Image: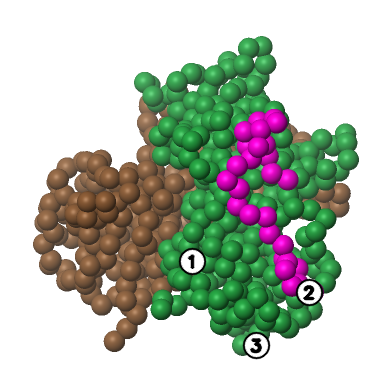
Chain colours: A green, B brown
């Protein structure tokens, strides 16, 4: 058959699939006190995308559409367009538009607008709160708060470029964002739909292995921790390769080129997430040039050597 | 012989600009003799060798990491550049500038974000870097930002510039900037740019370069937001991984429309890492949104293409 592979990139060479910044470290911990159900960076080893997951490492947490002012406030409503500027179809069987943020928090960035008749051009600091009742991307509308009350024109193309997250310093530190809480994609009191499955360890002593980045802080004492289940580069890779999963789990070894020895082994489940044999929280310590290597297909019950 | 050469099965829209972190939009072809096509980003050979300031992350293009220091009684800051992993920048490394450094003259506006190690405090201000400025000296490890505030950023604390769009003066001539096909003075005035990826051009009759085009976001004024790269970032990434030996100076590509099955046009992918098509004049290509590039065979300098239309 066609052979399964993972990219020969370092953790640092790769990119977070849940927000557009690169990866920094591996991290493992216990996933029962919370719900690991991200909609971004979700893909099966045989190349099937899931949830709101899409291919561009850049168009994650971005928004395209036209805007309309909200009287006597500095808020704007954006009517969402598809990524190619085509119309957004809410009937499409997906939790929300592809790339929609998959966590509750206040994402701050910049609304940019280019005015078609004269190629005039403006840019304002803007924030979208995915917890807000006005955050209804699945319905094709989302609400931004803003620098100005007059600047943006109607019927002209508008882009939100995400930058970092934000938090209220008056209150409890690192209270937002909540990374493992999904937004109400369709507004309040309406069910999220077509979600990628929640994940968890299904073997004794195993914990999830997270690919972790630290989101930028515009202001406040945000909790900038952001873990994804698969590096975006892996989503991209699996999608291309579409190599048939031959067994329950793909056994990966993490190798150090420097010494040529294996540092640890892990399970890549065909569902598209990783587990390691370890108990407790741990930021993994790794050779900066170390990479993941696929070794064999093994079943539910292969016992992993411990991580350390 | 060897590992077979391939190009990714992505659409233009599925792919990403290699010269600024936004996705591709259209194919465009035109004449490349009135200007110098010598970008340092999205430059890679078909057998996987990165060139110029080209690097792998589609996100870390036109970004800057380092620490900052205020410039007395102005709202400008000087950033002392760090490598991508926050390690120290080595100007002795044989590269035009740090990897991912902007490869065009213009005013790039974004946001400087800073996080205070001790207490996890954060702040973020609107910022602009002008790559034409005499203070834009990335190869020496320093770059200058203009800013929202005069007191906020602390010294010795990690700082990140996240690019957003480009900018221009509305009082001045329109579309006069940025200048996409003009390299910055990577080492300041008074010093030569060094270790550049080669300039490129058509070397066959009737052929023009084929550009992978995006339109950069405009912050304000009337900027010229056109941005063409020679290879989609996804191709750089792909070639780097595959490292498949070029078997010829050129790889013949066909652009196929999958529902129909038919070929829309053919083009030459040169092992040097740029594309040409047989056509004379400017033209935004019109393509089936789900059409993709397909590698067909290795052919030599002199294979005659069939006109694009």
How crowded pointer 2 is (Cα within 10 Å; few <14, some 14-19, many 20+) is rated as: few
Q: Which residues are magenta?
A: A181-208
Q: Which residue is mark 3?
A: A261
- Residue B132's spot in the image, x, y percent? 48, 43
Q: Earlier in the sequence, mark 1 or mark 3?
A: 1
**Circle 2 chain:** A
Badge 2 and badge 1 in a common chain: yes
Q: Is residue B29 above or below residue B261?
A: above
Q: Specify the principal SS of the magenta part.
A: loop
Q: Tell me which residue sits at (51%, 38%) in the image.
A: B165
Residue A46 is labelled as 1
Instruction: Indicate yes or no whether the magenta region holds residue A65.
Output: no
Q: Earlier in the sequence, mark 2 or mark 1?
A: 1
Badge 3 marks a residue whose secondary structure is: loop
Instruction: Indicate yes or no whether the magenta region holds residue A204.
Output: yes
How crowded pointer 1 is (Cα within 10 Å; few <14, some 14-19, many 20+) is rated as: many
Q: Residue furthest top?
A: A72
Badge 1 and badge 3 in a common chain: yes
Q: Which residue is mark 2?
A: A204
Q: Is residue B10 above or below residue B289?
A: below
Q: Is residue A164 above or below residue A197?
A: above
**Mark 2–mark 1 distance (CA, rounded to whole Å):** 26 Å
Q: Which quadrant of the rendered structure holds the N terminus of chain B?
A: bottom left
Can residue A126 be seen?
Answer: no
- Residue A266's spot in the image, x, y percent? 67, 76
How crowded pointer 3 is (Cα within 10 Å; few <14, some 14-19, many 20+) is rated as: few
Q: Tell me which residue sits at (48%, 40%) in the image.
A: A92
**Mark 3–mark 2 distance (CA, rounded to whole Å):** 26 Å
Say whether residue A307 is left or right of residue A191. right
């Amino acid at each position: 058959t066609k052979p399964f592979t993972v990219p020969i990139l370092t953790v640092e060479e790769m990119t977070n699939s849940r927000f557009p910044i690169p990866l920094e470290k591996l991290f493992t911990g216990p996933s029962s006190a919370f719900v690991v159900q991200p909609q971004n960076g979700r893909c099966t080893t045989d190349g099937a995308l899931l949830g709101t997951t899409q291919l561009s490492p850049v168009d994650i947490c971005t928004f395209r559409g036209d805007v309309t002012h909200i009287a006597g406030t500095q808020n704007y409503t954006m009517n969402l367009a598809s990524q190619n500027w085509n119309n957004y179809d809410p009937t499409e069987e997906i939790p929300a538009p592809l790339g929609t943020p998959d966590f509750v928090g206040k994402i701050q960035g910049v609304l940019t607008q280019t005015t078609r008749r004269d190629g005039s051009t403006r840019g304002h600091k803007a924030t979208v709160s995915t917890g807000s009742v006005h955050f209804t991307p699945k319905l094709g509308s989302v609400q931004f708060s803003t620098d100005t009350s007059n600047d943006f024109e109607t019927g002209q193309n508008t882009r939100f470029t995400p930058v970092g997250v934000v938090q209220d310093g008056s209150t409890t530190h690192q209270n937002e964002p909540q990374q493992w809480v999904l937004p109400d994609y369709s507004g309040r009191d309406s069910h999220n739909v077509h979600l990628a499955p929640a994940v968890a360890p299904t073997f004794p002593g195993e914990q999830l292995l997270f690919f972790r980045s630290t989101m930028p802080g515009c202001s406040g004492y945000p909790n900038m921790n952001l873990d994804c289940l698969l590096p975006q580069e892996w989503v991209q890779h699996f999608y291309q390769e579409s190599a048939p999963a031959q067994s329950d789990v793909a056994l990966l070894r993490f190798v150090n080129p420097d010494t040529g020895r294996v540092l640890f082994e892990c399970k890549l489940h065909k569902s598209g997430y990783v587990t390691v044999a370890h108990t407790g929280q741990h930021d993994l310590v790794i050779p900066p040039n170390g990479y993941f290597r696929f070794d064999s297909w093994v079943n539910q019950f292969y016992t992993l050597a411990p991580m350390g």
